[PDB]
Amino acid sequence: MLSEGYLSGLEYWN
Amino acid sequence: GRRAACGAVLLTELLERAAFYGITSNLVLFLNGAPFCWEGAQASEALLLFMGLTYLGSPFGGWLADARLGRARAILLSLALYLLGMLAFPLLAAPATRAALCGSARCCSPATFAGLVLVGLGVATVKANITPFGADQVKDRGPEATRRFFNWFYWSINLGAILSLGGIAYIQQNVSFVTGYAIPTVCVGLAFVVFLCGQSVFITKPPDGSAFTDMFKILTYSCKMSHGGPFTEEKVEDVKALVKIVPVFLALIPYWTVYFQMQTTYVLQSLHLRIPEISNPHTLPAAWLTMFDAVLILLLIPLKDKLVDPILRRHGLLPSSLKRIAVGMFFVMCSAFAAGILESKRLNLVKEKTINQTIGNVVYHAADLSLWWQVPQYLLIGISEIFASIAGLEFAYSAAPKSMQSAIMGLFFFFSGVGSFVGSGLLALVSIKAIGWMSSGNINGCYLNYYFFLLAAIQGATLLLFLIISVKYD
Ligand SMILES: *[C@@H]1O[C@H](CO)[C@@H](O)[C@H](O)[C@H]1NC(C)=O
Image (tube, chains in turn yellow, orange):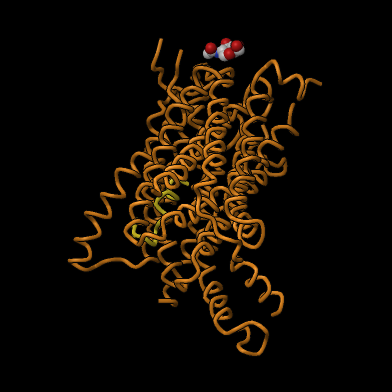
């Protein structure tokens, strides 16, 4: 998936 | 000071993502070629299984890294296996060395399955382990240092994927397959060398033990029970929270099926459409469509988070996570409908007019209709992604204790891989002779429109069930 780059640090408000 | 450790992690992730997306982009075209007499459905199923394995081995990779072995050692071993697969692929692509492998309708199935399995396991473990490792290398300084590091990580992943989908896909499609498949192998070799020589400057932690062991021990021992068995009340509460979270991913499974269709069957359709030529005969790469969607995602997530969200919060009327998930699934519905409509139009048109085009080594009897009408499907997939994939994790985090990250991500990836496996299984089920939907690499004699409509229908049933459940839940 292409969104996992954003999802990797989601808790840090990536 | 720490720039010698953060930079190594960033570079390793960039190279790994570049190699993975170089492999995944042009695998359908590669298999549907001269060395392999694979059909379109078989190649699509193979790539779907590969992606499903990569995303489903992530929880097992995390458990292997945490319960035993370690974190850095797990990444090192996974990089070794992934490089082994990256050596398997070009040795197979080169005509000279392909004889030693399979000289004497799947000509070299064992080699192309072993390589895919090894690459999938390596990618799964690296993807599951690199982000906690990168967080650990900078967590000492403070929250702002981690925020900067994860901005860098976000950008590194994006540029790795984009550079892959542009350059490596173009080279593989137009120039040659040996060089375009050796480039990801060289990238993996560079990443492995960087991690091996950069190991001394890394900050490593002993294996702590993931929550999966506690999960499985509680499940085997077993509303459950509190302070009655060996397990403490906190662990039981955490397991109950995870049980409450699971149904969201269970409903998101068809979403991930249709999403992972992006570069398995949509690529096949694009190959069977009229692809423009950009040189005196270098055709446009078929992976440039998903590269364009990725560029749209990069251009829109800052746009969304900085324009739509602030004024939405200021004016109210903000939607909850479940509403955003429903909107994402509706956009997935629309994407599947658009794919079905385009495929039906193409099949109706090709009945009288067809133009022979060559993409690599194989010749495709494409239709007259232009490729660019496939853009709406990819745009809808990207919008559905930004609406649903992020909202799912936001809801899961909002319904989980703050001490249980890397287990929400593990389950998320596991259910994504389950969705990919379900999509591959559905394609195989419609590939049987009893139904005969795809029992005719030419798909002109097949019926892909019916399969796309089936995906849309199952997504619709899932969405209606999700809405009915959510009305009671909310
Ligand atoms: C497509 O290729 C086949 C095999 O070379 C050939 O018989 C047929 O004439 C070609 N059709 C067109 C429209 O070029």
